Structure formats: structure tokens, C-alpha cells
């Protein structure tokens, strides 16, 4: 029963860990999710862009099973294992970072961001960090501070550390330009903190919870220029955009400038708990032995899954397929724009696409319309996710391995849900 | 080759992720670890107290495979699952908290400590946190601040947030008494922060990296009293001491006073990435919906493994067994105390036992002697771990499921390694 | 000799205490300063807007001597005196605060700002403070944090406290509007700190060292509105703009909205060390007995001088006079705007008037032209002061008591320095 | 009327500015204070150790009037003057700082400490500051954090900056030794902050508000040793102990080790608002020009007063007189220990002497007995001050210029007030 267990969950767990759906997952494969009462759903959430290679991809299951017949945990900081080194070598070969790449593995994306910040601070000896409004980087203390949304991520968890600031993110719909961001960064350097006291600038090439806003090329170039000038570490948070989501393996592959450090997680292990930081070896080697670590860091099962994820992305050509699916979804949303004026924007990159809804009679961002369209899709068996500053963005996070027929059915459902 | 991948590792990964052993893991079962060249080792590390049920316990592997046939990740905050709820119910039933309990799951122990601090700050509306010298609570920013050992955990990652203080932990060999701890707390209340601005007091009932120092009953009682008097949340970090290690399920079960919050990890899932926080349901309900979470939180495979772990500790009487094994180890160490004057102390609870070595001609802490015994034991096939402030303590973290014959062989090897 | 003592100065005092002039003061009266070698200077600095009533005003001197016959210091928090209370009563009656006013006295302007922040934190129980870029509020740690100009005030003195942020200040010449300020405040609320975690918003009605930028009426109204909505304390820093400088007694008297707190110093005692905070009695009474104080606070001689200063401002009609002299200066500057293309702006209120210079060919802010005009004037005997974000602003801080003929001589000198 | 003005004072000023006496000062000279109703009091407060040279010493009045006929304020950072340089040279010639000295002047002692910390931070590039429990250093934000007494100086003004810690001050009565302090410093280095991240260790040679505890020679030597070893700036806060109070010109003259920086105020100008920092020239020169300052800093009248105070201390042999008067008061207090069992301790240095009362029927610190003696002596026309962690200590801060007959009358009054 989904109601019995709804009450059991509300009684056993705190209200702080909120849950979107009131049905309980029973099984899942690729992009199909069945609950405990037999209802099937098309998963356009992918565990929040974690299942780019799909629920229980057979190669991932095979790799996890093979490793489960060897060992699940030795603590890498005690007894190492080759799979860690080989995955790090492959990431170094593929990651677009400055200089020669070195990679370390942790467990959660928040741990990856934390360690990127630790590496930057140890390299520069500086305290400051600049992030962007609307950015999301984790739910730990420091990663909350870096996160550019207060409600609900930061309510009641303050005070937050000093030397951490935010500048507005370029958004065409809201009149924020690249030059607005650069002016805010300059106002930081002239009012708040010395440029030679800022250790890192951290940014998402495509903001996840921010509404799938893409960083303009000028912005990435300017960030690279400022970091080169002032000795600041450039951090690209590719935790959500990484691994073929944006049409290339990493979102940063769409830009000429390379960041110094890059954080990875979610789809890195295709449904297993793994994260990592990859970047310039001169910067990564700043902490001494013992300065970085984590007990679950580089979990053998998750690392095997990540090897499988890389091979799947390659052999099934998930980058091109991400581009094709994103184009089809854009076509559907733009065609619907003619009949549903509430659609205010269609943005994104590759298969990282989102639609933002304004009230057609007011012009103000309306979360109500987004919620009701999300209700309609769900009742039709389509699981959609909400994001944005005002919670009026629907982001589409289908697995890149979703079959064509199921994707077309999902487009039909989305068309019927857009139009009342 | 155990030495070609050593160079590969040094070239691909950052220096900051330190590694103790020069060999690479190939397979592991219970307390037996086999490297890529075939060498066998008796694992007295258990992945740093993560494998209380031993490497790949058959029931844990069966549970993980069963779940692997259903789904590995749905993002719990999007789509929940019953295994999370039932595991929370079991932890609530077993946790040493006064009154109604509530449990939330995350992925890493540092994440659990972070959420305990978030819960305490949301409940009290205060900033301050008081921890203990020699304590270890994670490698994230806030958990580094709570950690009471600067070298090597905090070197280069400051500055650290305000309102976080440390008081000395009682140690009979170092002359620190419970009254010393309480006087330092009072000095904090009179010099650094008013008690009504302290949100939590976090402590390990048995210090992990601190040298297995056991908290006196008077200290736990004074902490409970100070917390009730000033409205401070009492946090017990049982990440390393939890799950049958100390002879009871949780170390706090050795004391009459119950904490408000308790953090769990490591052996909770017996080799899978899972952590948690259980406590006073009213305090746990302090953060509003949306304020707590984490993408991997309560990973389904790890949840299944944790169910298995609870059932294994029950059905195989691992508390009783930890008491027996700790007693055998203490007998071996005391029988050696007459031939080895370097044995300065033997401390701990249950099967969380450590031996501290001083120099037999100076009386000063001797880390070299401990490293030499460790060196000798590793050549005989026994993997031992060091800890303590001065690196002069050897901690015994054998899996609780180690067979009697292998344990007795390890005792013989240990007697030889102490022999000089 | 001015040289001998210049070298002795460099040898005995730190380089960090910067000194603008190469001559040493010997005598001073009203707006006339004589160096130790006999050279006379028309003082358009007034000790940085401290000598509004002019150097050694006879009434101030007579009051100071009369008190000197009584006592110079008793420590007010030990033994109080009636001059403190009567000055507090006069300030309470004259301050632009809604409802019952209370006034406390301290010694320096930074001390007044510090106590205003302390009062706001005690009244709200919140950590945060929001200030404006280009603002100056003192050289102590918290007041450096509030100051919105890094160079040179904050170089090497970090890190600075968390929960302290800055927003742009409206300027017609730099493209910053009131709505830009309000949007940045909203971005703070949405990205950095909860609105109901901000204790105060501190602002200058007329930015002193920032270039004499006048706060538009809409900005003050919006600040008042936000404070009423979020329960934030509205702090007006009138240390430099206060006491008849802007054509009315306080700059806030030009606006319909009233602040919760107002800080006073500089011309408060007309050349004696005294500061003060006046505001809402219910808010002022937030700190408990024993929370506010200062050994020198409300020094008797400075309090007598401040009594004299109020009586001088009233009897010699210094508000009206400030308006007249500001109009004469504006006539001179606007007249010169036809021959000097470098004159890009002439702004201010009353006798708080500044001219900003841009390059006549490029249009960029030209600090070199400003310096050039300052040296020309200095060579003719006119002591002028620089300010602005780029050091390209000349501020006119003559004593309001300056004789008309001396003012006209200074205007002629200024006209000569503006062209050739 | 003292009652009518008592009510007026409570009406016009905030409750936070606490006031000890309910009468209002009318006149004062040397050690005799007259209120508005004609009552005379022997001033054993000296405005909280500010009038070592006495109320309105004739030489100080003469210097102040001479300067008042010249100028009262020019803003030293705009136009300098001789008296600043000559006073700095005299301080450099007399101050016991390691190496050749430079001196800067400010206005309040809190500002002096603020600038000492600024100088240490600029010199070292480090954030950390270590202070002592029971120490008092100012009522500003940073000097609050440095202060080691929460009630009443810190209540409601948090949260406080990170990297600021406190260690116990050696006290014979409370069982705190030098080695306790050194162990707490080592615990800071091993649990809280790296030694190479601490910019300064600030301490009072004789704690003022803490109860006149004298720093033992071993403690000063250990602070000097640790500061030399780790690059930490050693700061002696002699705002209260300076200028012949302790029997030598500065308290540090009783010790063989020299601090790097020394802060001065209070008696520095003998009742006029002045403060200063004197220290090693190389360290003082750390902030770039424009980094240090203050509008009122180095007030000409106060600087003339400081010249006069130095001359008075020399010509009237105030150091020797401080020793003599301290010995006479100690004789009076020890002889009273026989009939007053409440006298638990009589401590101090020179004429910086305090008596600590415990309850003779339980052994508990008694602020009530101290206050009864205070009011008993006040009824007889003798004005005493309280202090201590528990408010149970009587301080004797008579002016050093007090005549012998008045001192003997005060001793008579003190003897009668000690007994019931």
C-alpha cells in the first residue's frame, strides 16, 4: 500500500527530508519505474540526472556483480585497488582541465565540491570563494554557503562562513547580462574582498536547480581571464551537467576555456554513490598526504559502475543521442508555445532542457501553472521535475538511453499536459 | 604487479589522498584479504571499522544482489522506497534516545555529522558548537572545524568558522580528568560564547582516531546535565563506535544518559556507502521540508546491506562475540606486558581495543616503536592500524565475524611482533 | 622647519599612518591654518568635515575652558555629569527619528557605528549587516567590514566577518540606479542570507569619502520600507554629513522617512573627540546595563564643545549659510564647466559639494587631472581634499563659518586652478 | 538635585550605558571629587585608572590651555604637527618593545588594540588571535571577541569571528598555573588552529577587569618563546597597567622579555582622550600607507596632556610613589585579614592592588560582601571600584598624586568599611 507507507515514512523520518511523490518505488529499468502497487511511470527525473545511462543498465549491473564477487570496501586510504587508478586515468584523459589532469574520488557531489574548495584554499592560501546566484553545490555547511538559493536549502542553518559571496548569473529572461556579472565581481573586489584574497570562483556551466541557464561563452572567457590575472582557481561544477548530458561528455567541452578544477558526481556512476574532482596537477597536489580522503571514497562497486558508464556512453553514443533527444523535446515545446502562451522560455543544452512558465494574464513567474502541468503528466504516468528560483521551471531529465517509442509517448503526454 | 600500479597511482591521483599500504587489493572475504600478487593478510583494519560483519558477508551479498535486481537509485527525495522506512523504524527501535526517535539517512559519516549540526542549529536557533580535542568527525569544512586534530586533517584548509570550540578529552595516561573537560567548558561559557548561544555538544563515546579513549560515565552524565540545563543538543558520534563494536549495539548503551542525537555510518552498511542520524523526534523535526537531503542519501543497495547487517549482528550474537574477542585480545596483551615494557596502556570497550606504547627508557610516547611493531606484523601477514595524538597507539579493528582459528593465529603473530 | 619634522615623522611613526601634507600645523583659527614656517592656508578640509564651526570658534573655546576649570574626565559609567544628559536631551529633541529618542555618547565615529551595530544585533538577535559600496564607516574591524572600499582601508586586515554584505550605491554618472541597489538587496536575500537574519542596513545619506553621492529619495524610502517589512534596523551614518553640513541639521532632514538609528561624530563637537548614537528608544534600550560603554565616552570637554556647537549652529544660522555657500561654489563650478571639459559632474547637498573630473578626450575617470588641480590650489594656498572610487573627485569641506571674503578668494583660486 | 537628574539620565540615555553612582560630578582636582550637591569624595577610581597624575594636574591644565590657544584638531592624516612626533619619539625612547620602536596614536584604547591586531595581521598574513580568560580589551566587535569575559561585555552581540581563542590566565587562588596556560595553548595548536596561522598572542601583564592578576615571569617568558618559535606577534595590553601604575613606567619593565607591540591609553593623557600603539618598527611598518588612521587620532590637546603626564611622572617620582602607596595599602589590608575572614586574597603590583573576598562561612566567591564593603565605604565618602570574574574583587585605583593625609584618611575609611 502507498498510503500505509506514506504514513509510516512520515512517522519514521523527519519532515526535513522532504519527498515529492507519495508512491513507493518497487522496480526500475532504463527509463521505466514501477511502484509497489503496479503502476508504471516514465522516469524523466533519472534520480535527479543520475541515471544518464538509465536505471540498471545491463553493463552496469554486470560490472557491479563482478566487483561484488571480489570486495565492496577496503578503505582506499588503507589498501588501494587498480580500478580507482584506471578510472582516474580515463578521467584525466577525458577531462577538460588546465595542464596535466589528476583525479581524486570521493562519494557525494557535496564532498567533491568541498574538496575542490579545500584544494583551492590549500593551493592559494586564500579564504575567499565567489559563486553565482541560483547555483547549487550541496547541502553541507560550506556547500550551502556556496549555494545561491536560500529557500529552502539554507533556512535555519546559519550563520554562514565569511569570505563567501555571490554574483548574479546571466539570464536572458530576467535582464541579467554577462557584464552585470562582471560588474558584480568588480564590486566584490572593490567593496568586500581583495582579488588576491579570493581562492576560487565556482560555477555551473549549466545551472541545475537554477533553471538550466547556460553560461554564455563571454562569461566563461571572462572567468578564465580573471582567474589567470588574479591567481584564482576556476572551478567548474559539472556534477549535474557531466557525462553526455549536454551533448558533449562534459558541459565545459562546449567552451574554449578550461577550468582549473572540475567536480563530478551523479551520472558519473550511473546510479551508484561516487563523486570526484579532476584538475590541474599543480593545484591538485597542494594538500599534503593525509589532507584529503574519506572512508567510502572511491567505492569499488561505484567505480566499477563508473567504468561501465564511460563504456556505455561511448558505445551507445550517448552524446549524439542527447543532442537528438534534446532537439526533439525543443521541437515539441516550441510547437506547443503557439497554443499555450504560459510557456515563457525554452532553454538548455543538449538533453539538459527546461521550460519556464509565466502567467499569461499577469507576466509574473507562476509556480501554480508548472505544478498543475506536473500533476497532469504524473497522472498520465510521466514523472517530471521542478526547479528554478521561483519554482516555475520544468526540467527534463530523461535517461539518455530511453527508447524512441517511450520518448515519443512521453512527448505526447507532455503535449496533452501543456494544453489544459 | 603491486609496484607498477604504485607509480601509476602516484602519477594519476593527487598526493593529498594518502595511502598506507604498498599492495593493491584483489579479493576479500570475512577477515582475509588477498592482493593482486596472491599474498594473504589477516585484516585487523576492516576498512577502518566499516566491516564489523566482515568482508562480503553472504547475507549482505545476497541482500545487495536482491536489491540490484530491483533498482540501485531513485533519488529518495523524489521517489521513496520501503526499505528506507523499515530501516529507519528498526534504528528508531534500537537507538539509545529518550522517547520517540526519528531517523534520516545520508551517504557518508561526515554528511551525517553535518546534518546533526544542521538539525541542532535549526532546533536551537544558535550558532555555537563545542567538541573535544582528539575527536574526529569528518573531512568536510564544518566537520574539519569540529575535528580536534589539526595534523593532518586541517592543514591548509582554514580559516575555520567561528563559534566552534574544543575542550580536552579525559585520558588517564595523559593526566586529563573529567573535571578538566568541565572546567574548559565553563571557561568557554565565561570567555568565548554564552551557553545560550551554543547549539550542540558533539562527542565520541569512544574516540576513533584519538586512540580509543573511553568517555567516563561522569563525563557523559555531566554533558547530559549541561545540555538539559542550557538547552544544548547532545550529539553522540557513533560512526566508528556503532554496531556491536563495543560489546553493545551502540557505545551509548554503556551509559545511563541518552543523547539527543546520534550519528551512524561505517559498519552501518557493512561495506556500502550509508550513514544516518537518529534522535529526539521533536528535535529531528526542526528543519522544514526541503532543508535536509542528498542525492545518494539512503542508497537502496546500502539500505539493503544495512538491513542485512542488523540481522547478522542479531542472529550471530556479535555483541557477545565482540566482548569475547576483546577479552581474548586483552589477555594476550597483558600476557605480553611482562616481556615488553613498551606496553604503556591497554584501553577500550568490547572489541574496540587499543594498546599505547611509551619508550621503556624515557617514558615519552614512542611512535617509532608502534610503527616497528606494525611493520613486523605486516611482514607476518597481519594488517594493523595506528592512531592517537602522537601516532603511538595501535588499534585492533578485526571484523567481529573473524573465525576463532584465524584470530588465534593473529594473536600469535601479534605476540611475535611485540617481541624484541 | 617642515622638512626636518617630515623626516622625524617618517622615522618615529609607522608608514601606515598616511599623511597628506608636507607642512606641519602651527596655528589655526576658523578657516585659516598657519604652518610652523609662517605660510597661511585657506582650510577647505576642516579636519575632514570636523570643523563645521571652524578652527577654535570663540564659543567652543570658552565652553572648553569653562569645563576645564571643572573636570576633564570622571569615566561616565562610573560618575555621570549633567552636561552629558542635557546634550542627550537636545540631540533626542533634534534627531530625525520617529517617536521617543534616546542618545548615547562615545568617542570616535567608528565607535558610534560599532555601537549602532551592537544595538541592532541586540534588538534583533540576528547576525547580518548590509552596507553600500563606496561607504566609509571607520577603521576598526567591524567598521572596515562595513566599509565598501577595499583599497586602502582593508588591505591586509582580513579575513572579515561573515553575514556582512554590500550593495551598489545610486550614481547617475556610473550607471547605478536605485533599482540596481534594490535588486542587489533582493539577490542578497535570495542567495546569501535570510531577510529575517539581517540585523541592520547601514547607509550614508550623503556618501563622504565615496564622492559626495546623494541618496535619492526613492532609495531612502525603499530602505525604510524593507526595514519595516523584515524587522531590520535602519542605520543612517551622519558622522560626516551631520550638523548643518548639508543645509539642514542632519542630512536625513531632507527626506520624509526617518531611520531607526543615526550615528554622529566629527562636527558633533567641532574639533573635540566625541561621537554619539541616537535613535528609537525601544531599540536603543535593547542592550542590558553593562553592555555599552567606553572609558573616554562622552568626554566632558567634548560634551561642552558640542553644546557650544549646537548654540553656534543656531545663533549664526549655519544651515542657511551652508546653503548659500554651496550655491556660490556651484555657481563657480558651473561657470567653469564651459572652459574645463574635464568637469564631468558637480553634486552634493548644502555645503557638502564635490566635483568629479573625467578625461576630456577618453571620458574615463581622471585622478591625474584632479591631483593636478589639487596641487595648483595647494601652491596658491588652498587646501583641497580628494575622494571618490577612482580618486578623481575633489570635495569641498570648508568651515561653514568661513568669512565671505576668504570664501571669494578661495573661489578665485579655484577658478585659476581649474583652467591653468 | 541628584534624584531629578537620575531620572532625567534614565530617560534620555539607553539602559545599556550602565552607571555606578547616582550622584553627578560638579568639580574635581587631584583625588577630591565634588558632586552637584557639595558632597566630597576621595576618588579611588581615577576614572578607571585614567588619572594616575590626578584630576586636573596643573601641568596638564597648562599644556592643554597652551594648545587650546593654537588648534584643537587638524586631522593629523591631513596636516601633521610637531607634538605628535615628539611624543612618539619619547615613547620610542621609553617603551620596552623588542628592537627599535615606532609609535602611532589613536583615540580610544579599544582602537589601540584594534590597530595592534591589524598590524599583526598585516605583518604575518595570518587570521588567528589568542587571548586570555578574564582579559578585557575593549567594547568594539574585535576587542569584544578578544575580551575574556562574556557577562556583561559580550551578551547579545554575537556571533563572533573565527580564529579568536582564549586560554586560562595563571591564578594562585583558582588553581590555574603557567603550565595550565601552556597546555591550553598547545591544545589550541593541536585541535583548533595551526600555530603558523596565529597572528598574535595578546595579554595583560596585570589584568585590569580580571582582578589584578599578575602574569608570572615564566608565563611571559613562555609567550615570548612561543611567539619567537612560531612567528607570532606578542602584544602587551598596558592600557590600564601603563604609566607608573605598577611601580615602573610600564608593567613590562618588571620582566626580562620584551613584547613586540604594546597598547597604551587611559593614564597616557591623564584624563584626555588619547591612545597609542608602540612596537617594533619593522612590524609597525607592515600596513601600507593609508591602512591606519582615525579622524580624532592623536588629538593635539590630548597629546599635550600626554607630554605633561610624562613630565609629571618624572618630576614627581610617580613610580616610586606608586610602590610606596601600594605597600601602605597592602599593610592595611593584611592587618585587616586578621579580623576580616572574608579577605581571601590581596594581590597586585605597585599601586595596582586588589583585594578578593570569599564568603567566610562557605568558601564561595562573594560579590555581595564586596558590594557591602563598597557601599559602606561610599557612605563615608570613599569611592571604590569592583571587578573580577564573579564581581567579588575590590580594585584600588587612587591617583598616584594623592596626598599622604588623604590616603591615610582613606585607609581609616577602608578599615572601618572592612569590618561590620
Image: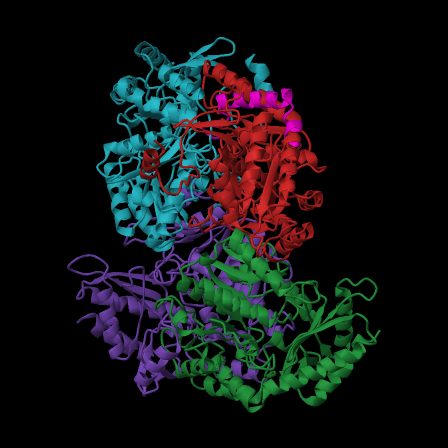
Chain colours: A purple, B green, C cyan, D red
Start-end of magenta stretch: D294-323
Quarter holding the N terminus of chain D is top left
Does residue D142 show up? yes
Does residue C370 show up? no
Residue C95: quarter of image: top left
Residue most extreme to the bottom? B315
Q: Is residue D408 magenta?
A: no
**Residue name at image x 65 percent, y 61 percent:** A289
Q: Please, what is the dominant secondary structure of the magenta stretch?
A: helix
Judged left or right of residue A18, residue B274 is right
Residue C155 position, x and y percent, is 51, 38
The residue closer to the viewer here, A410 or A1, is A1
Residue B28: quarter of image: bottom right
Residue A191 position, x and y percent, is 42, 41
Q: Is residue D306 magenta?
A: yes
**Height in image: D341 above or below D246?**
below
Residue B370 position, x and y percent, is 75, 69
Judged left or right of residue B184, residue C146 is left
The residue closer to the viewer here, D11 or A248, is D11
**Height in image: D80 above or below A318?**
above
Residue A251 position, x and y percent, is 43, 61
**Height in image: C130 above or below C310?**
below
Judged left or right of residue A365, residue C168 is right
Residue D233: quarter of image: top right
Amino acid at each position: 500500500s502507498n498510503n500505509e507507507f506514506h504514513q509510516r515514512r512520515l512517522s519514521a523520518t523527519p519532515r526535513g527530508v522532504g519527498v515529492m511523490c507519495n508512491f513507493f518505488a518497487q522496480s526500475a529499468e532504463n527509463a521505466t519505474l514501477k511502484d509497489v502497487e503496479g503502476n508504471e511511470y516514465i522516469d524523466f527525473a533519472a534520480g535527479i540526472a543520475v541515471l544518464n545511462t538509465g536505471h540498471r543498465h545491463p553493463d552496469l549491473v554486470a560490472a557491479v556483480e563482478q566487483q561484488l564477487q571480489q570486495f565492496t570496501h577496503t578503505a582506499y586510504q588503507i589498501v588501494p585497488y587498480e580500478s580507482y587508478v584506471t578510472l582516474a586515468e580515463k578521467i584525466n584523459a577525458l577531462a577538460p582541465v588546465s595542464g596535466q589532469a589528476k583525479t581524486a574520488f570521493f562519494t557525494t557531489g557535496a564532498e567533491a565540491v568541498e574538496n575542490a574548495v579545500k584544494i583551492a584554499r590549500a593551493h592559494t592560501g586564500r579564504p575567499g570563494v565567489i559563486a553565482f546566484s541560483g547555483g547549487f553545490h550541496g547541502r553541507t555547511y560550506m556547500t550551502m554557503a556556496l549555494t545561491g538559493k536560500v529557500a529552502p536549502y539554507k533556512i535555519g542553518f546559519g550563520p554562514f562562513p565569511g569570505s563567501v559571496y555571490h554574483v548574479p548569473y546571466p539570464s536572458d529572461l530576467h535582464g541579467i547580462s554577462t557584464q552585470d556579472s562582471l560588474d558584480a565581481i568588480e564590486r566584490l573586489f572593490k567593496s568586500d574582498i581583495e582579488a588576491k584574497q579570493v581562492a576560487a570562483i565556482i560555477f555551473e556551466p549549466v545551472q541545475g536547480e537554477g533553471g538550466f541557464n547556460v553560461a554564455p561563452k563571454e562569461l566563461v572567457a571572462a572567468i578564465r581571464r580573471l582567474c589567470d590575472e588574479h591567481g584564482i582557481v576556476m572551478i567548474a561544477d559539472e556534477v549535474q551537467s557531466g557525462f553526455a548530458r549536454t551533448g558533449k561528455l562534459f558541459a565545459m567541452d562546449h567552451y574554449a576555456d578550461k577550468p582549473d578544477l572540475m567536480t563530478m558526481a551523479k551520472s558519473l556512476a550511473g546510479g551508484m554513490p561516487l563523486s570526484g574532482v579532476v584538475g590541474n596537477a599543480n593545484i591538485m597536489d597542494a594538500p599534503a598526504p593525509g589532507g584529503l580522503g574519506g572512508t567510502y571514497a572511491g567505492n569499488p562497486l561505484a567505480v566499477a559502475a563508473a567504468h561501465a558508464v564511460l563504456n556505455i556512453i561511448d558505445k551507445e553514443s550517448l552524446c549524439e543521442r542527447a543532442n537528438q533527444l534534446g532537439q526533439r523535446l525543443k521541437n515539441t515545446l516550441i510547437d506547443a508555445k503557439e497554443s499555450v502562451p504560459a510557456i515563457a522560455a525554452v532553454r538548455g543544452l543538449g538533453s539538459m532542457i527546461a521550460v519556464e512558465f509565466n502567467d499569461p494574464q499577469t507576466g509574473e513567474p507562476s509556480a501554480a501553472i508548472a505544478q498543475k502541468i506536473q500533476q497532469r503528466a504524473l497522472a498520465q504516468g510521466l514523472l517530471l521535475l521542478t526547479c528554478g528560483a521561483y519554482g516555475n521551471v520544468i526540467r527534463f531529465l530523461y535517461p539518455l538511453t530511453i527508447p524512441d517509442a517511450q520518448f515519443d509517448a512521453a512527448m505526447k503526454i507532455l503535449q496533452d499536459a501543456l494544453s489544459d
